[PDB]
Image (cartoon, rainbow, N blue to C red; front, side, top):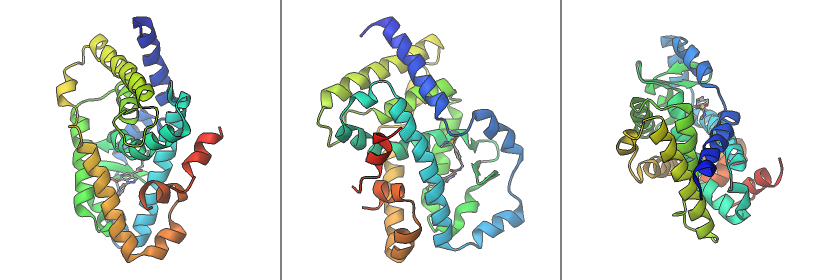
Length: 256
Ligand SMILES: CNS(=O)(=O)c1ccc(CNC(=O)c2cnc(OC)c3c2cnn3-c2ccc(F)cc2)cc1
């Protein structure tokens, strides 16, 4: 590894993100004045548990699909074997989405962008998972305080995805070398932009692991109560990543 190569990797990672960020930051920022009304919130609260879950499961799948395209565009990711690629995406995709979510979260009124408008925690009351929603809202609130940039999210998410500590990796050292280069790339950007201060302020080791395990646990409660709802109305990719291997992620990696 060399300096100008690490300098190229920073450009390679920010371009990958810029292309697959789903929604531009300004589009999210200009819609912050477009908040859900008291009557509009009540409507979501009056919706059935399974209809709210179906909508959330879809929006989360929409979000993950861009993370899968971001993965494919990452430097070195496609050089890894199909096993390692799936291993990393199965563990990473939901963590990356929760990191990216802080862009759609407005710290001032404590609201999040959802279905064209900004709404508080109460908009998801029908899901019957109060704790998880408040956990997701607080996490977004912590990353908001960090005053992140788009370039910073790009390099940080790339690191969240390329973790050599995931079980199931056959070519571990190949992931270890890519993780290292990406680590140096992120640290070099922070050093250049005089933003190394955020390193101590970043989320703890398994903070994101807690939100994902909470998300899988809260889904298993819903799947027990409504098994046919999940079988018939939930997105196939969502079921492969969170219900229980099916070969949907392989179809996404093989093409494009
Ligand atoms: C992720 N990329 S982005 O450009 O930042 C971006 C961000 C947001 C949106 C539109 N909002 C959402 O997708 C959304 C917002 N808030 C949520 O909850 C806090 C969501 C969302 C999707 N699933 N969930 C959710 C997850 C787990 C759960 F148990 C219940 C709901 C579009 C695009």
